[PDB]
Image: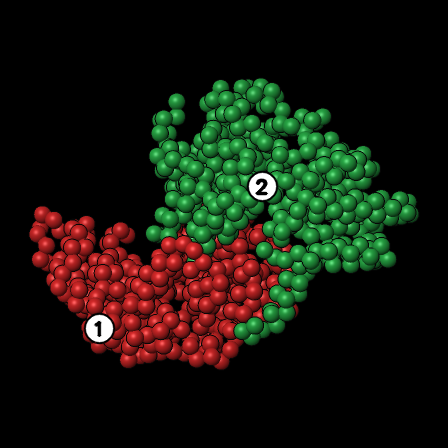
Chain colours: A red, B green
Amino acid sequence: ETDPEVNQIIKDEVDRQKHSIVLIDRMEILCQQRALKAFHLDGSRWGVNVQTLSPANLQVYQAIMKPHDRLMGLDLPHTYFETMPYRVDLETGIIDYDMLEKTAVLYRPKVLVAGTSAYCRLIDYKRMREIADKVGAYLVVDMAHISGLIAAGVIPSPFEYADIVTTTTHKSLRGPRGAMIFFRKGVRSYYDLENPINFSVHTIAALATALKQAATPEFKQYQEQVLKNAKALENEFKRLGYKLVSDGTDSHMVLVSLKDKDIDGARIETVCENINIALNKNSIPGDRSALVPGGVRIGAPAMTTRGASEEDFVKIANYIDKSVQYAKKVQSELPIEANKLKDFKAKIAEGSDEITQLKNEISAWAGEFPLS
Amino acid sequence: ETDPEVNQIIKDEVDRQKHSIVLIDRMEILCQQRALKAFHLDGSRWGVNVQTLSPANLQVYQAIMKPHDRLMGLDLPHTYFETMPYRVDLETGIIDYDMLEKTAVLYRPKVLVAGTSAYCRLIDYKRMREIADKVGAYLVVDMAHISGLIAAGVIPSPFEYADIVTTTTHKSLRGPRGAMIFFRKGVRSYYDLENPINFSVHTIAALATALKQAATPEFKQYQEQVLKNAKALENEFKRLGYKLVSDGTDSHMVLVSLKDKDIDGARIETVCENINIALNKNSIPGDRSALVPGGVRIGAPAMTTRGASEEDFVKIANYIDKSVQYAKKVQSELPIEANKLKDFKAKIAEGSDEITQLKNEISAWAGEFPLS
């Protein structure tokens, strides 16, 4: 490098990535144009507030609702504004639109928000609009995790029905670290969102290119692959006998249930961590304890960027199944006096022949892919 | 570029800079070591909380003081915590330590903060400590604008007397955009700052190098030049008959008074803007209106980085004097029916022979310097 030992730390970290499968003024005006073009938005119906120095959703709430007003979102708490959650149906994993409607009619929120939590299926934005209208609420859609899918046009757009739409520029949209808040202009049913939003709130070159890239057909090819790779994963987990939350996915990620395997997702996360597989434990509907998450969240985008295919993702599913089989083994073999998660972690941190086998196998396989 | 028209916007902006004189996990552990080494800090007496994703001072207040507790700082308002200001002596421009002490003894703040406002002289951190002890307050020093000067060792260090010290990593310290909060450990008189501070709260490679560079003798040479360049400016403004706030500077910036010239700093800012000179209007002690700032703030660091010398800064002073002489002319020649700042701005935006002369003169001179 230019000088320091920093060079080696970057070298070591870059090298660890390569051998791991990851499953997790005038320029400003240009960003506004490219943002609207990326999401096929009429400039007279839709405005947009971009920002590189930056939460995004919190700024929208303080802009539009008073301290008396109340908000509804997926799995929120019951801080400054009043909140009541809505939930997925326990048996199907799909948003319970009936209960949402009924609660919203009584609760009468000022804002109805969607896309906050980890939800693999498409959201019925039309039904969200209809529920929001009955109450007279704003419909805010956080599209931060599916923004790339929407830009590509490979899933439906919330911009047909939303009043406000928030997104990060860095997650699904593949740009630099910032945020964008889209808002409506014109006939509501009247709109006065522009001023309060703008009032409530080096890399802008980066974002401008990232918005241009987002509109390309090469980008759409990538997002098509993301959806395919996530489906391949859905089907192999189903074939290997796992239940999925929402019985599958319409998007870039899968949420695997582990209830039927008699094990939790934290245990799976740590086993995977030690064999060069990055994924997240994740709470699922049905869990007895909020501190013990009964599922695992797996996402396709990172390896798809590395040139991975459905064949590679069917293989990833097997490696994860192998990791649950190993986690089941070691947990059952732990003594009853030291059974807890702490003891499981201590045990796995010691190593084994099987861990070194799997790590080396996964490491070498992962090394075959480049960082595109 | 890689593709877009963005290329030209960067080209045009870079070109405008060149012809303008500007007067305004393991890696984390490495940043902590280098930060302490940069400010010659014993690791057992001083800790540090670094952060690239990021206000810094607000986090310190919420950490250390309850809602009953109160704060004192230079020229604060009388939002969530109680604040009372202290001020500079109207006639000398130096902090009125007598009045601070007297107010602090009565007010009894939990926190005494220094280095918040634009103050060109050295702060008596020892006297701040002594005042803070009499009350039992914490002494928080914001060194964001003089951090580079302190690292070089060319001015006294607040770390001898402070309990907490905040800084941005990007202003005086010449690093990437982030923040650091230093805090004490050991015998207060007892310290319990580490946990509450840490609890209250890609480029980290950049910061690590920036902290290494900050400790070099080449960096110290740069800061020595900054102080020299700012002094050259102090002396030429004095020679040309201007009063300075605090009758001069002990630091990287000068604050010029314009009261004796019968003109305000906003008018000077706009004239300078139109002749490729970037500086800030700035309020000064004595001002009748808070909306009409009676001074101008000029800083040496930017051109010093471009290889500028005292000879160049004595020339900069003349260009600014020329700009006040022009601003006096056009304002006196405006009709009484359209005298206001609005009318002054309209007038200057039209252009003139003198503006084009000065812009071209300043532009060509500025073009001689590189962007080192």
Task: From the image, tell me which residue sits under label 1.
Answer: A318
> Which of the two discs, 2 and 1, sits closer to the camera?
2
Label 1 element class? helix
Three-letter amino acid code of the residue under disc 2: Glu
Q: Quadrant of the N terminus of chain B?
A: bottom right
Residue A113: percent from the left, percent from the top?
A: 46, 59
Q: Nearer the viewer, residue A185 or A329?
A: A329
Three-letter amino acid code of the residue under disc 1: Asn
Query: Residue at horizontal 49%, vertical 80%?
Result: A217
Residue B34 appears in the figure: yes
Query: Residue at horizontal 62%, vertical 34%?
Result: B250
Query: Residue at horizontal 25%, vertical 72%?
Result: A364
Q: Nearer the viewer, residue B164 or A117?
A: B164
Q: Nearer the viewer, residue B32 or A97?
A: B32
User: What numbered label is drawn on residue B224?
Assistant: 2
Q: Quadrant of the C terminus of chain B?
A: bottom right
